[PDB]
Image (tube, rainbow, N blue to C red; front, side, top):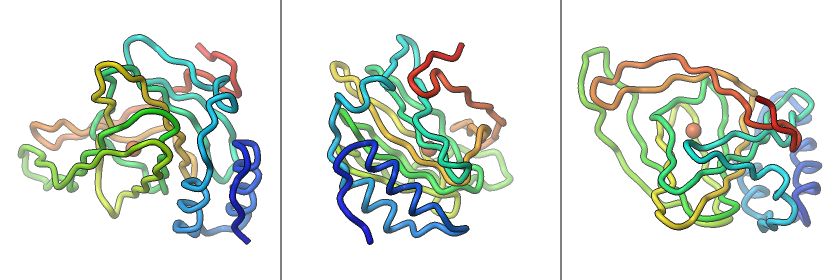
Amino acid sequence: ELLKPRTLADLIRILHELFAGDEVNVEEVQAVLEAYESNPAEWALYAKFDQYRYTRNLVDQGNGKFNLMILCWGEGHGSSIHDHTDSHCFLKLLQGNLKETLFDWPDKKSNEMIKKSERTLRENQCAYINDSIGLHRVENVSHTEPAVSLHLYSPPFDTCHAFDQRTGHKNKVTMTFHSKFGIRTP
Ligand SMILES: [Fe+3]
């Protein structure tokens, strides 16, 4: 029975119940993520920025079923065009705004990747993506406001592909955590 998360800690407890089985009810996970009202005091520990690019900060390992992490986006910071390695990916805004641009999977032929759509994700909104939906790029286009987002990936993954927008060619990238459980991990 899906109740409103009172705090980040309560949210994490609810997610462990939702991921207790072998499958994922996407709409229920999205609904509970959206229902958590961002409270900056609860996640300040994980919000560790870098001057030059966005940072990934591990919050919870989900008893092995999912990774929950906080991403911190300085002004102008963005991602590659990327896939999600056959995982579910949920993205909830905790602070600021992010622009999400969707792309189709490239064809074998080298060609410019054209965007299919774009939207602005605003505070407390939760977006969802998986490989069957397509690829995306996520960017903080603000010149004045850092953004902070809460990401849930199931199953967890530590590698994905980055796509060259000019050709559609991909390269495997291994992502690293900036911090884990509030502790910087160089
Ligand atoms: Fe993504």
